[PDB]
Amino acid sequence: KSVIRWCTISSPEEKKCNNLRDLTQQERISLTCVQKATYLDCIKAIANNEADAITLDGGQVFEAGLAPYKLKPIAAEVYEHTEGSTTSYYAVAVVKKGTEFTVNDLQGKTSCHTGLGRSAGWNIPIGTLLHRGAIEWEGIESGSVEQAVAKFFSASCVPGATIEQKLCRQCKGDPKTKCARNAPYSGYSGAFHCLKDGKGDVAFVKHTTVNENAPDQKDEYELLCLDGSRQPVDNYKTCNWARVAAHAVVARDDNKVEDIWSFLSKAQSDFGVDTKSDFHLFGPPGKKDPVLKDLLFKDSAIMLKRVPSLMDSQLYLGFEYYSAIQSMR
Ligand SMILES: [Fe+3]
Image 1 (spheres, rainbow, N blue to C red):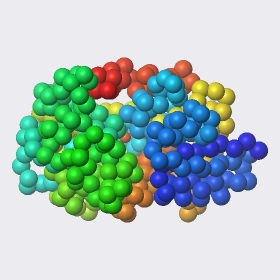
Image 2: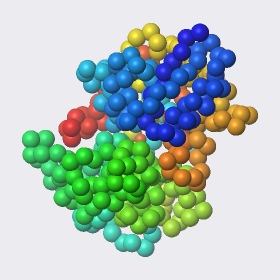
Image 3: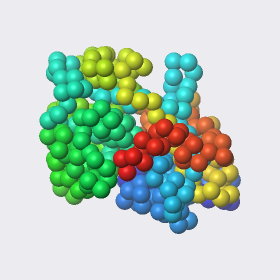
Image 4: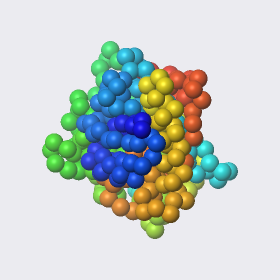
């Protein structure tokens, strides 16, 4: 009857979306999938009524909420929390055991990031190191944050970086695709593999990333904490760089939001973590090639929760994280 258009940003993603399309062809709200080059092309397409929805990291919810787009988060991913579940996660910095540098010794190291402008992979680590005085950046007029970061680290893999060569030097893949936002070393799992393969000394990822990727070998890794110590991977509640809002589905502020939520509400009922189907909407998490990870929704999401309609992107991210992204922008 009514169709919603999901906007995807990679070929494994479009494939996953088209599999869900085939499984919901008999539902009152059906699905079709369009694929774009980047999440930004998807924000443009949705604001242009060529697509209806996409899940975005908190840093990208920020951009989606800006004029001329003015898309709003309509549903948030929920992650497992010791006390039930939460719509937030922790940004951590993962290093290997037996290297011995602290957060104060990061100058000249190589680094692995989920993507330019993402919460855990960029906004939180780069924003924190500017605040601590480690990365010297004197405002946007002084040039880009990319330039300041490429001065700090000796080389990096930062998917989506465009000004600095050095920020794509450590990425794996074809020349044309190695530093793309859907490259091999992109996302939480991609940045973890960049560290595992020795292409970075530190990977800026989230609290579930080592479990999702090397659960057997997680004691070969540890976390770099803000107080200068190193703690085990499971000690992220006391060794994290920030708690950030969950990834969220964004949409135009118009009446299609109810069709999108009814579609999502039913799809996680049928294909959620307790599904009897072979199709999983969320993950499952576990070792597999990183380009197959966090497709449509993160592998670590366990449910979607409706966001109150009165929350826009600023209220969703919170005033403090919103002004932190505005000050690096
Ligand atoms: Fe994220």
